[PDB]
Every structure is written in structure tokens, then in C-alpha cells.
Image (spheres, grey):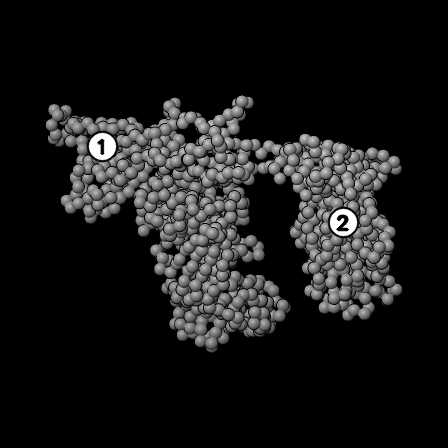
Amino acid sequence: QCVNLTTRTQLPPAYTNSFTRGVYYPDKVFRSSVLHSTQDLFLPFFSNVTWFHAIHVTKRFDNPVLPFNDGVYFASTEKSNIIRGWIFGTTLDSKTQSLLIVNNATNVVIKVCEFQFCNDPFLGVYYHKNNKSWMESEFRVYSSANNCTFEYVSQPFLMDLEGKQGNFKNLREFVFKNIDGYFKIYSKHTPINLVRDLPQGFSALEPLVDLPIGINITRFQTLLALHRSYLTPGDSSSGWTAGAAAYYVGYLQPRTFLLKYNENGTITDAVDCALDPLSETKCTLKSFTVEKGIYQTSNFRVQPTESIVRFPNITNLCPFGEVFNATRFASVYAWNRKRISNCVADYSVLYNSASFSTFKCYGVSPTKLNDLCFTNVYADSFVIRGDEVRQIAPGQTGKIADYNYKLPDDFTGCVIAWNSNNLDSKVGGNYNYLYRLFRKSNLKPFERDISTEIYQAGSTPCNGVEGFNCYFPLQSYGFQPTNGVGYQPYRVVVLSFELLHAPATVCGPKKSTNLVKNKCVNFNFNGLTGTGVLTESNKKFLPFQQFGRDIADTTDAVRDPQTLEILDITPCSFGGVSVITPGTNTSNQVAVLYQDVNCNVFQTRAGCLIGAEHVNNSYECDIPIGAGICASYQT
Amino acid sequence: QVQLQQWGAGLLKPSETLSLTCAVYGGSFSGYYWSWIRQPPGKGLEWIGEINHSGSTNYNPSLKSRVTISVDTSKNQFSLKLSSVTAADTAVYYCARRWWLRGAFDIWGQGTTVTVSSASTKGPSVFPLAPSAALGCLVKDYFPEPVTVSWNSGALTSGVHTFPAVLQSSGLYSLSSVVTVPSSSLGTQTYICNVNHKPSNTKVDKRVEPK
Amino acid sequence: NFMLTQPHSVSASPGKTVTIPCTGSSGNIASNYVQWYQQRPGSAPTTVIYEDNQRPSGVPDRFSGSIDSSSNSASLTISGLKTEDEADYYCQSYDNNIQVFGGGTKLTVLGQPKAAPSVTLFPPSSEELQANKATLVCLISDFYPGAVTVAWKADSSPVKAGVETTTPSKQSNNKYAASSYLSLTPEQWKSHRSYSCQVTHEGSTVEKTVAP
């Protein structure tokens, strides 16, 4: 059941160098007298690892919740075995299952449960002089446990219930690693007689257990036994004591290692391949010794930093202002059409104008048409009542749709409209606008009908002059300025887009970035797409030529669409790294050559040599570098 | 892809000025419409105003008189000032993007709460609600939340309820509790409301009885 | 100017299908695009229909928009209701340099049996009458879905002053509860020779009454 621990005086956690520590047997395979390469989660060599304390001098003890990352390397130098085990999980709060280890002299209890872990998880351990023993008085680790799914008891560990002193005579160290719902554990124990810290020498952890737990892990926390000694009040204001233990945490990560297995089937030495250039050389040769010489070992390669895209100036804008800002619009029965072709259409000036009362598009979203292309666009335009703007859409009906202007049911254009009673309304009405009130039949899509002859309303066969059942087919609108909004004039434009087998000629504008030079960049010049270093040029193309090619028929120059300048393209496709070694019998220092790159360091014909001094004194060649240049080990 | 992160002063009192900032990651102010919307507690959304593409501003006529919205492109940040605040300005405030003038509210800031309150820590009045034997306790005009209640010092739990607290027109809260027993049980033991109001360290075990 | 209106609540049983209407008024809803946003409680809204018919990427094809200029209305149909559809839905449109939103509809998927509100009303506190006030309380409980609204009377006539009222929220047994208070003076309590509190809930209607 849960309690708290006093919030405290403390110091920040320290760091220490891991040296060679934290190697473990990757596989249950016997291999003897052999060097084997493997890519696995390891603690990389010489890593700084966090050092934590558990000391009552004041009151600095350091068991936060910590990340698990890819996996944990843990170590302890021994005390009262103050570390009792660990909890691992995600939410820790019963609602997600978590793994508990507790490592008691009675039982190594291993449990997965819906543990409700505390504000401060610990074992309350009291010196029961009542019965001449220390004992746990209190499981202050959790409030409740439920749905456990797994439990195990292993044999009582090399760790004890009493206020003992291992006094750093032993180093206990572990790897914890969760993969595919299998929680692996590894460990080793080792006598030490250093003062403190991780020792230099090599050792391998053996497998300790694997638990098929399946549960989510993200975080962990170390569990401590806290000394409610008889001098303490036995409360949680101050009725506890921390002892004086120390523990270390490092993290695994993906690394390639080379392991030396001896005759007895034991790992005895290792190389972290990614550490330094000699480690990469040993890992390349699959050997722990390297003879005097030069070894090709890796490839250098530069990556593009930016993408530029660049297209000719935006200039030939389509005539929309001549349609929308026109002075005289048509009567709807005799609607105008204008045909738009061979231009850059910037629809943005339409679709985010605030002026229009209606704006909507069918088969196309405004979020796409500024990057779309068409053979032609038609703009149809006319004036109608505010009510009738409803009917200018697919599948509509009534006098305007059926006798004046019919859209296809599968239309792919836009309808735009705005109120006007300024251009096109005055006292007595402007009667200059008309519509068909009568026809024998409905229009087909985009039909027009200017025909002006008397509509015979069925009965009374009519000899071409108006009368009863025989009406003139057009009516004129009463566009008074004081009309209600449904009877105000509205100017309308319908933009119909189309595609045929003819090439596209109306298209949205193309954006250009700035033009950048002397960096490796990705680029797109007017559709010509690539990656390289752009620089000015001495080439002289003919006025119509756009890009150059070499004798191998690959692109080596280009013209800028917006300034007509010629640019050379050069590849950043470098290669080759080599390590120069006096032999490991002689020394562990090395020099490195980058095979052909503009940068001690020392540029040469054969690329830039790094890490060795150039010297004017000639000698015979110890190790050959490039173009009459050699390297040697000297005072 | 694009993120909007917002922050500002979430607690105010009447006639002060509200001020929020919203900042964009993975995107640029220039091409798009950027807008502030608020949502009063348990009410419909209200649009406040916007910046258009290229940074001109348009405001809802109902807030036009006391709102200001502005950008700094050097921070990828824009902001809202709302002056002269009253209790009615209590809401959650969001920034949002729109691709074009009539298009959707495309992406949203995480939202931030604003409380405009005159109130400060003050204990309850505590009262009978005479049987009608469902019978009750009224805890009237207290602040802030929380408050705690039980009946007869824990001796009674039969047919209890504890309704949600009303945030009143005073800016204080009120809470009611009811307890329910047979028609025989009218005032038949120590009928009291054990009101504990720890925002003022207060406790009272106040009477409930038959009329 | 121009307003979108919505029903306050909608519900049907899971696996079934529902329509949420969004009605235009003072102008024509067909004239500009309509969007529907879903807001799940305690988070920013998200789009589910982004032009009158268009559905965003990743939105389930259970969601389906529509419009008709003949009713001057849009509507959203959700087909094959699920536990996760329970949310607020707001329609929205551009009008005249103003973005307008509907009032929002709560959708619940009808998991429990129907439940009418159990209602309770009490006399004002005697000790509050002594303290020169008269807060009656009308208390509303065990309803399903969480959808009540409340209507006080003093005498028999409706009263709008002194009324202060919660949103409905989920009680322990997963039904819903709410409370309403009618603050007056002792003279006003003695003046109002009865007190009453009508409750309406998914077409059902209920009452509770007390008097001096």
C-alpha cells in the first residue's frame, strides 16, 4: 500500500565514462577462436553514462522514473543491496500492466500486473530487534495489483534484506532489453577493489532470463529499500534513511560490433565499429591487429541542402477583367460567350474576391484549379433576378434554366454572380433586359435561342400575329432601384472548362523560388529536374538552345528561365575514404585520406588528406598516398 | 504537417484587456487566411475576425468596436487583443487557417481557456431544503470550487445525490445535495449537511428539517 | 443578415443511420459552399464535409453531405452509427465577409434504454427566508440521453428572472443530471402561491411542484 517520501535537498546526477563495459552474449551459439560481426543494440564504447547516488548525506538519493529508450545498461557497486529491483511499463498507474521485479532473499519475485505504483515506490525496511532481524515492514511500491497474466519466482539473488555492506567489493551489472514482447535480461557480477566508478577491463554479460510479457514498455524506475532504523521515528516526515549506495545508467542503441570469441567459447574482447577510424579499419578487415599500410574503408558523399524550382516570368494573363468588369452585359435569352485560350489564368483574383454574392464550382475545387490545365475556358454572361441565381446550377428547373440557359448535369465549371442595381437599375426600371417566358420545349445543355416569333399556346392555330392563346415569347424585367433583393438585378458569369485531344493552352501560374548558387541543391528548371552544384559559365548557347550535354549525352549546363544566364552543373557525387596505419604493433594513431574533395589538413592531387602534417622533407615511400606523395611514421 | 501553437493570459477580471498569441510551425503567413474563433462554455462557435492573405484585417461587426488582430512575420506569430472584457468573454479561443476566402477552417490551434471573473476566495452559505421524504441541502454562493458534502456526519447515505455546481451570475458557485428516505423518516435523526469548503478552510454541519 | 440553424440534439441506435439538418435563413444557403465540423468534447473541431458533398481524406464514407435550395437547407447523413460518432456537429458557411456557424447538434448513439427525467423540487430554505432570500431548487436526474431543458413557474405562470441553471452532465449510473435554481426574496416566495418546474426531454415533458 502507498505512501510518500520527503521532498528533499539534492545535487544533479553526475557522469562517468563507460570505457569497454556493457558487452553481452548476443546469441545462444557456441563459436570458438573466431571474430564475429553483429548489428545490435549496444552501449557504444566510451559513452558518458549517468551516475546516480543513494546517500543520506544531505539526503541525496536519486531514483526518478527514467526512460527505457531502446534498452538499459545498469550497474551497481555493492552496499546493503539498496536497489531491490525495478519497475518497467508506460502509464505505471494500474490502467496499463507493468512489470515488477523485486529481488528478495526470500524469493526473486517477478510479476507483470496492473500495479498502482506510488508517488514514491520503495520497500519500508525496519530493524526488527523484536525478532533480531531486518525485515520489510511495508511494500510501499504499489497500492493495488490486478489482472497479472504473468508471475514467476526465481532463486533468491546475490542480494539481501539486512542493512549489509558490500562496501563496493563487488560490481553488479545488467542489460535490460524488450523486443517483440520478450523482455530479455542479462547480467554479470565481478569483484572490484577500486575506490568507486566503472572499471576499465572487458567483461561480457550472460543471459539471465527472458520473460514473454508482451506489454508496452517506455519508462522504468529503480526500487529502493529504505532504512526505517530504530533511531528513526518510523514515519514519512523523517522516519526513514537512504544509506550510501551508487548506481549507473547508460542506454543501448543500434551499433555494429566485432566480438572475439576464444577457444572456451567465451567473448573476451570487442570493437565498437562506429567509434573512430581505426575501429572502422579493424571492423573492415575483421581483425584485432592491422599491418602497416593504407586501407580503403568507407565512402564520403554530400547531400543536397535545398530544392529550387524556377519557371519563366508570369506575363500573359488571361482576359478576365474584360468579362467581369464589362460595361454592358447580355439579356439572358441571348447570353454572350467569350472563349479564353493561350494564356495564364490566375483564378485567385476571382475565388478570393469579396465582391461576389455567389461563388461555387462543380467537379473542381478552388483549392486545385490554380495548378490545373485546360484546352479552353468559356465565359458565358448575362443578367437575371436575384431569385433566379438559384437556377444557374446542374439539375435545376424553371423559366431561366429551361427556356433561357441550361447547364449539363455533369458540368465541370464555376458559377459566379453579384448584385448590381447601379450599372443596371433606374426609376421606372431598366427594361433593356429580357428572358423567354414561353417555348415549345426545354433547351438542351448550352443551347441558345434568339428566335422571335409568336408562341401558339396549343389551341387557336395562329397566323403569325399575337392574340388569345398566341403570346409574344419574351418578357422584360422591371429592374426598379427599390425592388426587394429577390428582384434586384444580378450580373452572372459561368466559367466552363474543357479538355480535348488538342494540347492544353489555359493553365494556372507557376511559382519560382529564389536562385541559389555554389551549394549542392535539388533543382527544377522549367521541368528539367536534377541535383547538383550550380555555378556561372563561359558557355555560349544559340538564342534558342536551353541546356547543354557532354560527349556522353548527359546534362552539363542550363539556361535560367528568368534571366537567360548560362549555368554549369557539377555533380556532388564524391567517394572513397582510406585509413593510413603505422601497423598496430607500432602505434594506434592514424591519418585519413578523402579520395577527391576540396577541403592538420592538406589538399593534394589525390584529394584532401586530414590528420597528418605535410612536411617538405622527401624520403623513400613508407606508405603510398597519391601522385608521388607518401606518408610515414617519424619523430 | 503545419502546426499552430497558442498561449496567453487565461485568467482575467472585468474591464481588463485579453491578449493571445498563436504561432505557426512548418508554414508561412502570406498565402492564407488566419482567423480567431471562440466558443463560450457549452455554446456554439463564434467567429471573431481574420487576417487575409498578405495581412489586411476583417472583423465581425459585433466585436469590431473592441477587437484588434495583428501579425509579426519575423516570429511566424499573430495575435489577438480584446479590450474592456466582461463575464461574457469567458470562452475557449482558437486560432485557425483557411486556404481561401470561402474554404474550410483547415487546421486549428490547440485552443486556450479564458475566464473573466471578479471573484476571489469566499466561503458558502448553507441551507435546508425542506422535505417534499426526498429532502435536501442548498450550498449557495461560494467560491472557488471545490466544496465537499456528506449527510449526518457519514451516518446517512440513503438515496443521496450531489448535482453539478451552477456557476452563478454572482461569479460564485452553488451546489445542491438531496437524500431520500421513506415518508416515516421526516426529521427522525440528526439531519444535517456536512459542508466542508477547503478554499477557505471552512466546515459546518448545518441543519435540515421538516417545515 | 444570414443564419444557419440546427436541431440541438439527435440520437439513434448504433448500426442505424441519421440526418442532421442545417437550415439557412435570411438568405440562400445554396449560394456558397457549406462545411461540417465534428468536435469531440475537450478538443478542437475537425472537418468531415469540406464542400457541400466533398469528404476529406481519411473521413469514413459513413459521412455524407447534401444540399437543396428548395428547402433552403443543407444536411449531413451519418450511415452505420458507431460509439465513436458521438460528438457535436456544426455546419458553417461564408456569407458576406463573415463566417457563420450553426448552433451545433449533439449526436448520441443510443446505447442505454430511453429514460425520462426523474424530477425533484424543494421549498426555499426557511433559514434563507430568515436571511431575506428565497432560492428554490429544481433538480433533474436519471434521464437518457443527456438532453433536458428546464422551464420555471412561480404561481402557475412562467418566470425568467432569478433562474440559474447547469448544463446536463453524466451521473454515476451513466444517465444524466442537471439542476436549476430560482432565486427570489421571502416576500416573493410568499407572493408566488405555488412554484413549478417543467422539464422537456426528447419530446417527453415532466413537472415538479411546491408551494408556501
Q: Can you identify the residue that label 2 sits on?
A: A18
| Residue B118 in the image: above or below residue C169 | below
Q: Going by the image, does C14 lie left or right of A203?
A: left
> Please, what secondary structure does the residue beneath circle 1 have?
helix
Image position, residue A366 (x, y; %): 39, 38
Q: Looking at this view, is A343 or A585 the one in front?
A: A585
Image position, residue C57 (x, y; %): 49, 38
| Residue A150 in the image: above or below residue C151 | above
Three-letter code, disc 1: Tyr
Query: Count of labels shown?
Result: 2
Asked whether the residues under the numbered discs 1 and 2 touch, taking CB atoms below 8 Å apart as contact, a structural biologist would say no
Image position, residue A121 (x, y; %): 72, 58
Q: How crowded is mark 1: few (under 14 residues within 10 Å), some or many (20 or more)?
A: many
Q: Which chain carries label 2?
A: A
Image position, residue A292 (x, y; %): 78, 35
Name which residue lies at 61% across and 67% down. B156
Q: Looking at this view, is A198 or A337 the one in front?
A: A198
Q: Going by the image, does A371 lie left or right of A577?
A: left
Q: Which chain carries label 1?
A: A
Q: Can you identify the residue that label 1 sits on?
A: A333
Of labels 1 and 2, earlier in sequence is 2
Residue most extreme to the bottom: C130
Q: Going by the image, does A528 lie left or right of A127?
A: left
Q: Looking at this view, is B185 or A32 the one in front?
A: A32
| Residue B121 in the image: above or below residue A563 | below
> Please, what secondary structure does the residue beneath circle 2 have?
loop
Q: Say which of marks 1 and 2 sits in front.
A: 2
Name which residue lies at 46% across and 66% down. B13
Would residue B50 be visible to someone looking at this image?
yes
Say if labels 1 and 2 share a chain.
yes
Quarter occupied by the N terminus of chain A: bottom right
Three-letter code, disc 2: Ser
